Amino acid sequence: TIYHAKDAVQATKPDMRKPRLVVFVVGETARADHVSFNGYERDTFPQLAKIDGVTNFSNVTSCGTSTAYSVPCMFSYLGADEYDVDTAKYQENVLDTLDRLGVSILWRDNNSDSKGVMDKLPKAQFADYKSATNNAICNTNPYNECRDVGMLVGLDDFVAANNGKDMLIMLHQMGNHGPAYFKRYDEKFAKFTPVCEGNELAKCEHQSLINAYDNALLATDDFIAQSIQWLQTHSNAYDVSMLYVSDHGESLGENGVYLHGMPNAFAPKEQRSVPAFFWTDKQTGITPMATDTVLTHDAITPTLLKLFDVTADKVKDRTAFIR
Ligand SMILES: [Au+]
Image (tube, rainbow, N blue to C red; front, side, top):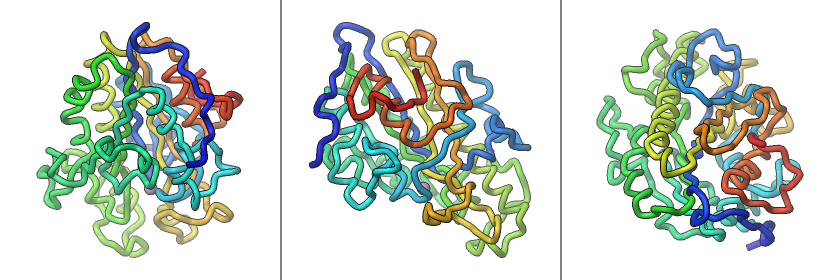
């Protein structure tokens, strides 16, 4: 292991102040420009719109254009300019640090896996929610695909087992993963019709492709809202907050490009312009940065440290999503 934050210290501890409980939704394939709050023509986040204390960040650029590249970068100490995907798994990352400091780290995954981020931590702290052995919400559609909201079931059990400790829960979404956007949401979210249902996306009618994509965002709006509602059930005992950031965007036919994964050197803007949301309860004292702050995935690690009152010199200078 190559360390970067052996100096990290937690300035206040959960025996001397309210324990802190944070959900970090690690999003998938969502584009900033399809978010209502960023000026999109459709109301793709109706439920998040009803919740007080949500900040939408309108200028966030991902570290890369794929899950394998972006996800380790989101938790890295090195920042986009120095990040090396090929050695990321041997670097101390922000979850390693928080775990060393006693913060209970949980990682539930309805996407693939943590792309190496959790590899140094006990395997019991990672749970596969793509399978009904863990996920109780899979038989709600014709494909029997486990839904992101199932990652919230049994979270009370985890909180009860970590009573009084600081907790950081990562929920790795299936989200808007393509090509089969139409599979990504239950029928209650099929608001925009007709929808593309083919694997050759260039052969779908463009509007029908957009419709499937936007319906998948409605299901993610629901999942994020439900995550906040779950946190709210613990707000008297815990200082609760929710961070959402997508791993990358998506091309939807611009210049004949589909899906993602374009190398950064020529990646179109749509693959790197991602949404970010931050919610916190009024008791926590956490203050969001300005909604239009120029931000990147580099802001994630200092945000997670600040949420737990941790300082590490490697990122002391670094802009976060919060003050
Ligand atoms: Au991804």
